[PDB]
Image (tube, one colour):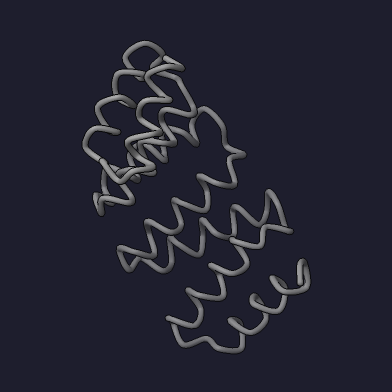
Length: 134
């Protein structure tokens, strides 16, 4: 399944999303509890705009590893892209509970608050993000 994963990665990198979904799904048939295949699938579904399928494989990935800040963040992103800001915040906060120094989670939390109109919170979360790396 590592070869199938690699094939999917290449097509995914070159934007051939439907070919990438094929190869990731083939990796899941060999190891149905493959974290990399499950995460990579949610990645392609998110990039495609299939937000229900992205949630499906992102929630499947969090079942096997509830400490994937990368998946926790991408689940929040998928919820933000479908306008569910309450769920998106909940997931960015889950990613910050795990790692309070997550620059993408802090940046994404400021982004959602800006979209919401809570600019006082947005400035607070954006400041936290720059307080890490210049």
